[PDB]
Image (cartoon, rainbow, N blue to C red; front, side, top):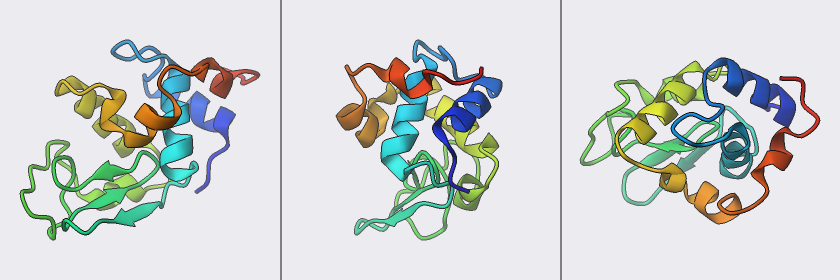
Amino acid sequence: KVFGRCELAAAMKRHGLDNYRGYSLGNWVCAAKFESNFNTQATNRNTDGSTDYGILQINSRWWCNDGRTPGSRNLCNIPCSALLSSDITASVNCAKKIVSDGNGMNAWVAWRNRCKGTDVQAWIRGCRL
C-alpha cells in the first residue's frame, strides 16, 4: 500500500506515535516519507547481508528476523515479513521498540537526513486527526 501523508498520520496517531518518547507525529510521517515514500512494501537489500523492510525501512540485523542476515538479534521479535504488511501495526510496534531500546530517531538515516531540525509539523498540517 502506498499511504497518503494524512492517512498515515491518522494511522500512526491511532497506534500511539504522536509525541511518543518525545517525537511529535510529523517526525514519524516525515521518516516514512523519506525512508519508503510511504510504501509499505519497500525493501532495500544491502551488501552486509541485511535488508531494510517496510514503510520505516527497519533493518534485519538488529530488529527483525529474515534468516539470512549475519549477527541477527531480532529485537522486535518479528519476522521481517511482518514489516511488509499493508497495516502498519508491526512497523509501528517495532519503531517503538527501537526507541525503547535507547535509540533516537537517529536510528533512521532518512530521519536524520531529511527530517531532523526541519518543520516536521508540515507533514501533518491540514490532516484530520
